[PDB]
Figure 1 (cartoon, protein in one colour):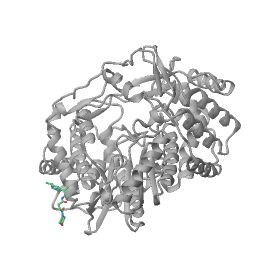
Figure 2 (spheres, protein in one colour; figure 1 turned 45 degrees about the vertical axis):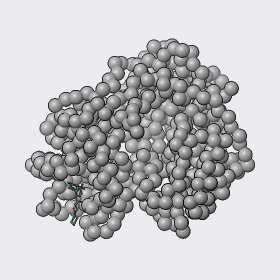
Figure 3 (cartoon, protein in one colour; figure 1 turned 180 degrees about the vertical axis):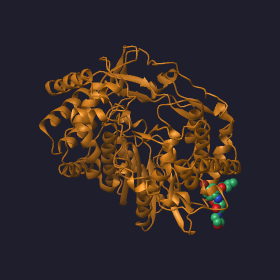
Figure 4 (cartoon, helix red, strand yellow; figure 1 turned 90 degrees about the vertical axis):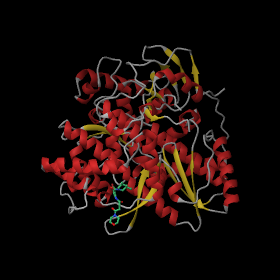
Length: 562
Ligand SMILES: C[C@@H]1C[C@H](C)CN(C(=O)c2cc(Br)ccc2NC(=O)CCC(=O)N2CCOCC2)C1
């Protein structure tokens, strides 16, 4: 058999006490009242996840697959990639990354302390000398926050990661490769090269370039678990097409054989849990690996399905295709052939794909294009999403300090949206004012990479990424207004009129502070007043070093870009 996992029966175990019910404080009810709708996943559901992820994989690889692969390799051959030094690798480690089993932590790595650096060197030397010994990994259950959807509870996802010293070695060999190769191989199809605005631009331009557009998202069931040894050796052979240092070629070969293809799973108590023969969800190449493999299989499946003039957009396991419609019947037939092809390549669907004839109704990366109007009254497309999970996570973060602040990532990514502006900005600026913590930098994630960001820099960060229009958008679409309102009903969030009222208060309190706080008041909350201020380009915006921001995806990859 080619089983994704085999298990010993040892349990997947927590590192600390786990909360599942929403923590409540004095601030909780101002945001939401239906507390029993919000939950965190815990290891107590890890057994259920183990069932879902454990299955046999069969792969039948045809001429389309090999044709597409040869093309990808030809493009990869044009990539030149560099080895990172120990220090450069060390500075990309998040301050709160999991510590080494070998008696040093993430801060020791970042400070380049001699015990960390000595060990990292010993790990590197071992990778070069040994290309066969399976590398130990830790299996953990992720604690993530959701809203119940009987339309109730998701089991915890799994995180599989090697030791801190190995992770730093992965950066040395592969950070430059994973940061640059995917855009070269996939071109405009590589989703992580785009800001939310550029993503929208790509999708709308792509949609308009078809005579009769049809689009679909493809949901692979348990994508990580569908990735086979072959898939992972095919990824490596793509990596080796690059112009690389001989030490990097050797480390990539080694990491592939010893880590990427598979390895033993160890719980937090040090017990052997079993064996993985699929994608590790917590390695540097998780995102890039998933993007390459998804694109390969999808492109091949498009050829199999004889889809006409198709354009793909791929972010890891997330896939959207836009092509030329052949009528509703023929399109449905094409999708079943596409799905059959993907299934043959070991990427069977969860939800079967369905043709869509309205761009706004296509969800990909949990997002969709929507329409609003700017200052001049012109129609503007922008990226939004269903606000349920952002608001459930916000409710959690209202009562709990967490290492990654999702509200802040969401404000950054969804700044032009009705719900991020009216609810998230209003709510969190209100708390930060009260606590006098406006100037305190908070950690957040964009495309999997960690950033340290000061909420006082939101106006200029937003201007740089979204333009000044993100502060002027009005007259959102009925479908969008209705989705937001239905979500507020579900969670028991105050209706929008209450938030407008609150934001005028938050705005005046910020203005009163003067300076950066007043800029936040001025720009972020101009929508809240009838008497509108003049929003001019912020001189600070042009000075922001926003390189590395929307270059690549690094989910699971232990990346810090501050
Ligand atoms: C009770 C709320 C319902 C929301 C849909 C809009 N709304 C807002 O406060 C609002 C919030 C943001 Br953020 C952006 C715009 C908002 N208001 C509107 O879209 C109302 C229409 C509006 O602002 N104008 C349309 C007519 O010309 C002048 C401009 C009130």
